[PDB]
Amino acid sequence: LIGCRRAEVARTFKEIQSLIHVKTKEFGKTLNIMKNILRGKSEDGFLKIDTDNMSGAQNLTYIPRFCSHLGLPMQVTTSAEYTAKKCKEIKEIAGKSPITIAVVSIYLNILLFQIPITAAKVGQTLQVTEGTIKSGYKILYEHRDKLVDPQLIANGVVSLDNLPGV
Amino acid sequence: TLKYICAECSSKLSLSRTDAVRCKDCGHRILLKARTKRLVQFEAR
Amino acid sequence: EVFDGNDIENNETKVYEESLDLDLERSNRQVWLVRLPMFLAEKWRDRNNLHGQELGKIRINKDGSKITLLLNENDNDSIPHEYDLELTKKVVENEYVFTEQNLKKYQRDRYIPYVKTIPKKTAIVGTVCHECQVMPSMNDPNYHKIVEQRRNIVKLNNKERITTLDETVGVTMSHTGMSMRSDNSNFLKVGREKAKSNIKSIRMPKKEILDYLFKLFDEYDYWSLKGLKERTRQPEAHLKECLDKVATLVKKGPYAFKYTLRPEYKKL
Ligand SMILES: [Zn+2]
């Protein structure tokens, strides 16, 4: 996980748990201890500026891989990346896990681009509860104007009425 | 900062240092450096 | 039916009601050894067919001993029904037919009384004097239906080409390597079925545990840590504190690495 985060290519905890059968508590404690001793060795040796490489969220780096798992086109992926970037401004979902934020942004832009993929398929592919995805879409329906890229709706490729209401 | 052209969609882009080399319109990861703006002299022989 | 060979105790009389001698009264029957083409051997050897019904007639023209088969129409219509039985040998020597039937198990001069002989009932079905081969007739209208079928033998391919996944490659690679999809199969979940067994016990008092150890030592003199632990359901630290007082481990005997009662308590 540290090697994935350092190369700006970070996977999630679920990925590493899918490969390595390790309990969540011991893996988190081990990650914390190794981050502490890595910072200590950096201070003792060559000091390294983090510049958002040990970032806990890193939700911009999950959008292309998660869109590839669903077989989405690129413009859906960049719209989802913009939506996930603008989701940080929303204080109601700022505490959500970045996997859930990425998934609800992807699902919002799937409904925006009329891609025929159901919430059940997104939940099955990315192992997020369908109720969680539906609640995230419901809580993001009030902020439709800020999340959707203004230049996309300006060019007319997508329109805000395509999103079903709650 | 520096001008580039995507290899397949031929869209002019401006990339800085921190920007990942990737087209913003079609996503092709092969980018060509823009031809220089200075005039270059050739002997016609 | 596995059985010992070279038995001089005549044990086969008691265990096998059927006689072991070869039956020879059927050896005088005449048997024609016939080689068939692919279709007649396919339809004349299947077990879902051949219920004893008649399959044809044999015509033997005595002008030149010409043998023909006139098959019945009950089998097919596309196949021919007139065939020629060519004889490649009018007299076939040293060829017989023997059959084997399972027995009924219910109700120099130096010799060894063990040769591993499998006793099976044997009977000569008859004598073979004619090696036969069945050709389709030239004049049959269905004869070409054989030949094209033979031309269908070399034409068809028994192997299919590889299947190409035509969907998006990302959907195919979603399940590969790094995936959010945790494995839900139960194949070889050895850690699931072995780490779920946990033993919990208390510090139950000394007199009852020593009486329990004496009961197990009376049942059998030699025991181990794990067997006694699962028999009495006690912690290892408490069980060890009671074993060394009344018992000891064997270090050099044939029953080594096992806890046994002390020689002072052995006569008790
Ligand atoms: Zn491009």
Image (tube, coloured by chain):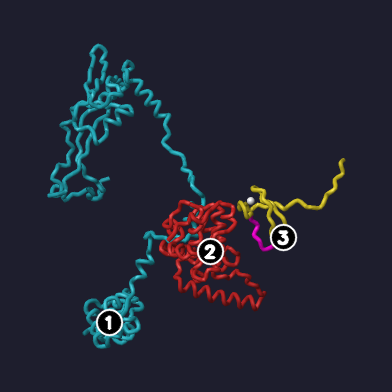
Chain colours: A red, B yellow, C cyan
Mark 3 residue type = Thr
Which residue lies under the disc numbered 3? B1
- Classified by dominant secondary structure, the portion drawn in magenta counts as loop
Q: Is residue C158 magenta?
A: no
Horizontal and vertical percent for residue C150? Answer: 38, 26
SS type, badge 3:
loop
3 and 1 marks on the same chain: no
- Range of the magenta residues? B17-22
| Disc 2 versus disc 1: nearer the observer | 2
The residue that appears at 67% across and 50% down in the rendered structure is: B11
Please give the count of numbered marks on the rendered protein.
3
> Callout 1: residue from which chain?
C
Query: Is residue B18 within the magenta segment?
Result: yes
Asked if one can make out residue A145 in the rendered structure from this viewpoint, the answer is yes
Residue A129: x and y, percent?
Answer: 42, 63
- The residue labelled by disc 2 is A11
Give the spatial CA distance, label 2 vs label 1.
Answer: 60 Å
- Decide: is C198 above or below A109: below
In this rendering, which labeled residue sits more in front, label 3 or label 1?
A: 3
Residue tagged 1:
C261
Quadrant for the C terminus of chain C, please. bottom left
Residue at the spot 57% in from the left edge and 70% down from the top edge: A55
Q: Residue at x 62, y 76 (%)?
A: A41
Q: Is residue A69 visible?
A: no
